[PDB]
Length: 121
Length: 106
Length: 180
Image (cartoon, rainbow over all chains, first blue to last red; front, top):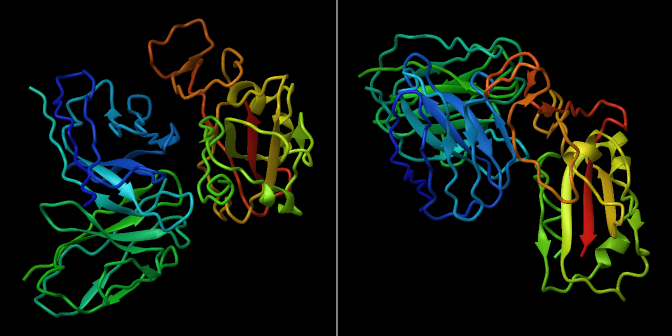
């Protein structure tokens, strides 16, 4: 129904960008706090940032400058762009959506989609 | 920073058996922590939000409390499913982080 | 059509101010006149009573949350942090401004650190310009090629909205109607 597909097929060579992209299959963006999450051994579940219908965002201060999220209001090709990809980022990423039964606080991650791979060699 | 030290680690059961869980906050969650579930192989899921309210879709037997140090989930039913990891979550002091979790076996 | 602008549960930040286009629809202001008694309705250019006789094509409706002691800075021809880096309104302004206290809807006991404003910036803005870039702002002589460090600041900072504060620091929801 609201399956959040991820069409970005870009794998990453060392130290280059992170050309991944999430996609929407039914649902309309509107005013929900779409976000991104990740998890790997070493350091498990992690939260990068969340985006609004505009550039409204708030990034993670563990890693902040490299991660630069985008917004696509209509074509909804919002991406999690990254610079200076390391040999440690290798992990399964995920695409996160929140529930609209609350106030201005992204807290309840409900809708989720299958993840992606990245490796260096 | 916000840290969680969820315990215990070793557990074993079978269908329709007792159950117990806890979360170990550090400074102050008030009433904004959350509990999640992620079966091994697919995406995670949400169990409890608000620290005293069950979320939609979650069946009848799932409820917990919270006071920054004395969280209590009183459940004693293990269906043919639900033996998987349970994930603690907390978000009141930026940034928000999840827990690690534990397991139970047959 | 005055529904999503006023009765909304989510308002963006000052540096990411929303822009909404309303057109090709009857815009009866019956709510405006009855919007009382905690709605400051300072209108610049036209009288509040003389609105029905006028007609407009594009009715913009901005909306954000700011501090009380900063709402004065929304008036045309003013200087300040909110009026120099975040949102600029031209001197020849023709529009209305509505501000109301929103403590019960945009405050939290711990503190809602979700509202952002750019503190410092190298150049002042131009009329109706969007500021979405979050690049590193450098003031020192050492040129940092996108590298964090001293004299290479990150020009974004969060508010400290809380309920048990003074009226000046209490959050205010402001909506500005600009008619073109």
